[PDB]
Every structure is written in C-alpha cells, then in structure tokens.
Length: 64
Length: 64
Image 1: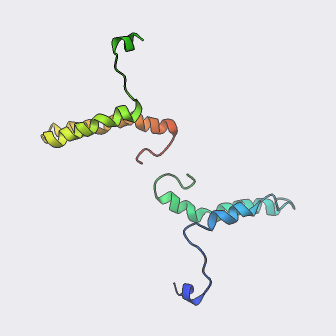
Image 2: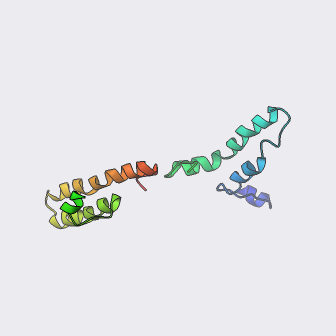
C-alpha cells in the first residue's frame, strides 16, 4: 500500500488492464521468426493468469 | 398425437416442468414437517437433474 502513496502513479488491479495488453500484443506483429512471435504467445497467456485465478476461484470458469 | 389426443393438457418443459412442484413439495415438506418432509426434500431437487442435463445440454454451470 505504501507504493500507492510512495508512487503517485498507480495502475489498475482486478484484471481491468490484463486482457488489454493481451489484445494489443498482436503476436503476428512480431514477424521475425517466432523467436518473438511464439514467446509473445505464452506471454499474453501469462498476462491473463491474474483474471484467470480470480475468475477461476469463483463459479463458472476462468475463461468463461 | 394420441398422447396429446390422450391428454389435452401440455406443459412448458425443462426446469419449468422441473422447478415448479419442488417448491410446493418443499412447501409441503415445510408444512408437512414430518419425516415425510424429508422425501419432499429428497423429492425437491430430483426434478432438477435433467435441468442439470439441460445445463449439460447447454454445457453451463448447473449450481448457478
């Protein structure tokens, strides 16, 4: 919490930002090999574990 | 036909068919408050299994 006062900047929690970068990532935009284009794919995946477990731990699914 | 010709009444199906009586049944069990109430509890949700199957049929969260 001190970071909230220690940093005048803060950033949204509760998944709001999570799906965004994933949407914005546009994995094909890395075209070089798939060195990047594949490693960005697990990335947007790794991004969304934050909503996952929260959507997970309740009813429905995480994805749902 | 001869079943409709048998029976000239017909019902909105699914959980509508299912969820209707359990209440009255529980309403009975609540009112009847015997140990017969316990079947009317045991009776209550047995209506909802095909709805569970219906919730299977849609492929959704049943408990919800």
